[PDB]
Length: 207
Image (cartoon, rainbow, N blue to C red; front, side):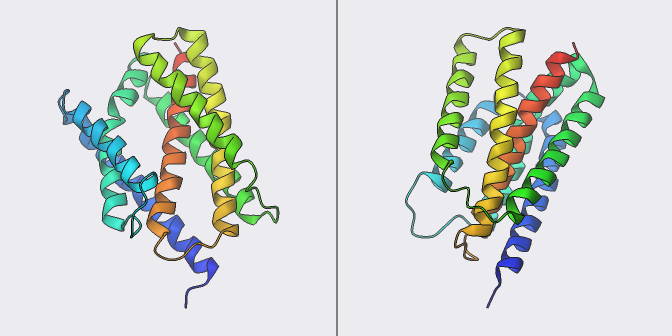
């Protein structure tokens, strides 16, 4: 008979582990040749769909989440190498550090506060819709410095709020032990998205 404390603890452990794994994948990524990046990104989107938007009998398991962390780490390499090339590695490290303390603080606040933040879920989803939209727009019509910078500020705010919300709902919602992997996956996505936004912002700012 698990308790909520143990469930949250296990979720956070898996989260940390996905961080380490994604880091291994990121390291691995510097030897991954281009054109494999496309099918890997495709696999990434398909896995996101299978895990979140597809009414399945059984929820996503540990193998799924850890594999995703690996591949995701690999695929965030061009982003990292790019911004490191124009801003330097220390900026990447500082962005990771920033993401880290933001996640720790906002996560602790979300998890330990008594209010139920289950009302802004629609607002948050809407925000993510916007960010994804301008993100796709960026592919066909690349944004300038100021624009990408603004997009990064908004992204930062949004995903920070999403971290707060997610830990809050992990505390408040009825989370069974079979949802542990997909919750940890959610925290991973929060982290990675915040990180990409911060890295983009400071990376551009330092060039």
